[PDB]
Image (cartoon, rainbow, N blue to C red; front, side, top):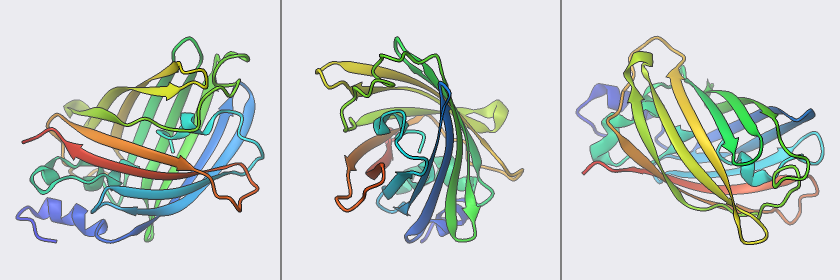
Length: 234
């Protein structure tokens, strides 16, 4: 609403208020093809996202929690004193590409590519996912993960050569037997437009997610409430 930097003002202007979100994912894991659609809203002022996802092809062949990170960082809450480090909003409305490789310890990997941009007043996240080398009897294809999600902190670094950012972080998925399945994430983001963007100093994002179900829904789905907040700069 009021910043002395016009570049910051520009990005913030698009995220004042509640913004509708559409998510589309086309996936293939070990030859099992699936699609996911999601709809909801984001409120960057509070770093809050509310979304409902549906598997449009039938039963999802992988556990829902494994897709949380793949299925919109522009809705993170950046404190006032850190607004100059918000790469995600600075790239809007043209958007950015988000690419990842996710390695599941002692199992397969996911490779993802997404485009995040505005289509009118709607923020769209379009994703392609390819999963290979998964074990038939493993925790993923075997559906042995609990339907929940742990809080975690993720470090963000600038990649000055690509005019983007990079991040590497570990997600721990709880297994029904009390154990854990590690998922090592490697991420890179680059802008789609050719205009300038804000490259940040090192910092982290604190995330918390709550997974639920819609009691009236017969389709395979996931309801997600996510909070993301930036920190690490005093």
